[PDB]
Length: 203
Ligand SMILES: O=C1CCCc2nc3c(cc21)C(=O)CCC3
Image (cartoon, rainbow, N blue to C red; front, side, top):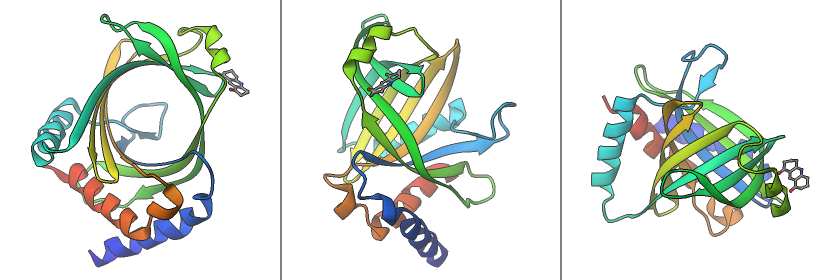
């Protein structure tokens, strides 16, 4: 609780220099190390821990605004094209192209038995929509079924991702700001840690 105030300060001092950038994004991702063979950190939760994080979140903030969206992502030469989805789950029309550049990443120390936490600040710069002419299947694809709960300046993202047949579960919290420069504060970061640590520690 005092040590949590210190981490929040350490995070703020590292990222403050970046908030002047347009299109800045901040997120905390639950995950684990050495759960797949090619990767170090994998941003995923078990099917069981996903559904009780879902039950927790949906009772604790039932008043909160909520949305659900199915989208079709295709990665192409470092850019991400997002496609809307029809009844069956198939790509229709491209809705956004962004390029994501990681500006700062930090691994958060967690309690024993909890999911690992990864804090990242990046830029997601929108792009020229005429590149959508490459179509929804010009590269590796990800079908995302996202549940989104917004609570003040915090958005919870629970996503069932189907890639290459296998389905995985992702849990992240993002910053929701009218202006990241003014609003993303140290006291905000400390609440991010507090809320993210809650999710990581059930059971
Ligand atoms: O929108 C832009 C800006 C110009 C450079 C650029 N290059 C690529 C894309 C998008 C953009 C893609 O969507 C994937 C292919 C490479």
